[PDB]
Amino acid sequence: AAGSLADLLSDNRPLLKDTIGYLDVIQAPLVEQKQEVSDILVQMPQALK
Amino acid sequence: ELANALQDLNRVLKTTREFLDRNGGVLTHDIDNLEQVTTAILQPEPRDGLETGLHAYPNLAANVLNINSPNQGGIIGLPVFNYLPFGMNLASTAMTLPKQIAYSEKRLQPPPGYKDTTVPGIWSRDTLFSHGNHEPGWIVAPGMQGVQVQPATANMLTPESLAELLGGPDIVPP
Amino acid sequence: ESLPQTLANLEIVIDMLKRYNKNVEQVLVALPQGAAVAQTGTIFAPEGLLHFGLGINAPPPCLTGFLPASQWRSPADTRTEPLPSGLYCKIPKDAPNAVRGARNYPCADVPGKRAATPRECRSDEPYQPLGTNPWYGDPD
Amino acid sequence: LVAAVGFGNTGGDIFERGGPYLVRGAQDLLPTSALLDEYSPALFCTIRNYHDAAPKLAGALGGNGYSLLTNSLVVGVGNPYVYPDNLPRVNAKGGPEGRPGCWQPITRDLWPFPYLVMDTGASIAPYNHFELGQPMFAEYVWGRQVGENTINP
Amino acid sequence: LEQLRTVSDVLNERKQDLADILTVAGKFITSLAEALASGPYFKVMLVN
Amino acid sequence: QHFAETRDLFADAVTALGRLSAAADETLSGSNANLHTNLQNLQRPLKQLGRAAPYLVGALKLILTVPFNIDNIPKAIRGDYINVSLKLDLTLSSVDNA
């Protein structure tokens, strides 16, 4: 298990770093506009019906 | 072997302690919320709803893309005992132009001397008498297996490409 | 008791996406062209183009498998009602009318079968139409 | 030692319950990951264009506040879908110019959207000229109609 | 992780709305897409 | 003497760590390369979604229901029937294009 974890980290450290950065940049507008997201999620089912 | 192992074990224990103290509550909260939302959207009725959505939406996308006519813009729709015994359709106006058609995959572009038809990938001959399945020599785009055709459109399709609509190998355009 | 369930649910979702990979690819293809279509059809900002089709009763619409005529509601009532389920045209694939309807949708998981809903794609009970659509009422 | 007993038991039970799920999920994610990677360029421009067309369609809906504003000019419709030739297909792939992507924004200088044909089982590509609808006349008593159904009208 | 936390909070608050979205969109999409099936257009009924 | 007193506890500790590490190793080895391929694939869509993140919330008004806008569904559609305003335009250019 120690070897497997060390290998996984050594292989996926840069990709996980880039994924963390891109998740940050994706989620910053989502957080800054959370009220709009909540409102449209509340609004959609009645419109769909 | 042992000195480096002990030192690195000490350092990783300290780092794990700090990392847990800093991120554990938020990480657990994220896991709990993700579990709750996924369990909510994977209930029986949401499950079959997502099933039908993925089963029947791309057809809707294809048809709503087919309704739009570039020359006139926008969409087209026609008005509608259940109904009258007789029906009529005077003519079909020009929806598109030869200079407006673009092909999703470069394998779908007709070669010289052939024109596209209302079933994608089936290419017909472009002659003056080629209207209403009347000019033989139709060839089929590569990788278009599994499309049934009516006998009338099969007659003009040539035996090789007619077989290709049921058989494996794709024909070679001239 | 949460991380195993999170991983199980993610596995279920990814499995359902994998069994319907072609559908997702088709939708991802159709979306940008849909954006281009909307951009083209909204050149005039307050009013969007929507033409009408000439010709009378070229395909006659089917009333089989839909709500009966006696169950229709007058246009005056803006009151909403619970939308029923399992409503689609029930003709035995005949006629030019509604060729590409629900009943001819490809089943992604089960090759070589076309049915309206995956509940009917998976079910092995044979698909029979509710009836041919007649011109003199009683579509049943 | 006692803390190791507790931690090992708890982690072992967690992994026993949630290891096969993770393994098979990461196995089934490979095709969809490749799918989403292939259609990367059709994401930013698509989101931008839908965002920009959201107010333009919203003004059309809300300019009145009680109905929809549309221009209705009479046009002729194409031939009705025929039974075997026009069955649905879900083999659509690719984008404009053979690769996934978006056009440039549709201004008024360059109005018409270049039509895109995809493996579907239906198209309106050949309608480049005026011709009479092949099922010009029909009957719904004995189903006897004039004209010949075609995919090449 | 914190911005993911607040996003997940606002999404867990509306998980039931998401379930209702999927439930209704799975029970009307087939009936609604039925209209654009007879041809390269969609049928309409004009009661006026 | 102390070790002989706590031999059973040491055995339990080693067996528990082994029970954890067996499942951990099987899960990590069963998904070492699938995870790497999934991440390498998903890196590009993550970058593109980061580019298009600010416009995402606005696009949700239209990207699901494309012909309609969710904001104005209740007022335009009054139940069974959709209210539409018809401009039957018989302009020369409209007929020429039609």
Image (cartoon, coloured by chain):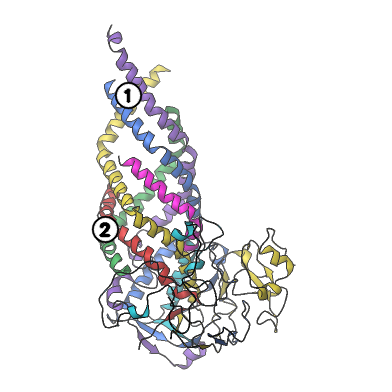
Region rendered in magenta: C1-27
Q: Is residue C137 above or below residue B66?
A: below
Q: Is residue F36 above or below residue B12?
A: below
In the figure, the shade used to draw chain B is yellow
Q: Indicate the chain coloured blue by its letter.
A: D
What kind of element bears circle 1?
A: helix
Q: Indicate the chain coloured cyan by its letter.
A: C
Tell me, for residue B10, which label it has, or none.
1
User: Residue B47: horizontal and vertical position, in percent?
Assistant: 38, 55
Frontmost residue, A35 versus E25: E25
Q: Are the residues at dot 2 and dot 1 in contact (C-beta closer than 8 Å)? A: no
Q: Indicate the chain coloured purple by its letter.
A: F
Badge 2 is on which residue? A34
In the figure, the shade used to draw chain E is red
Frontmost residue, F86 versus A32: F86
In the figure, the shade used to draw chain A is green
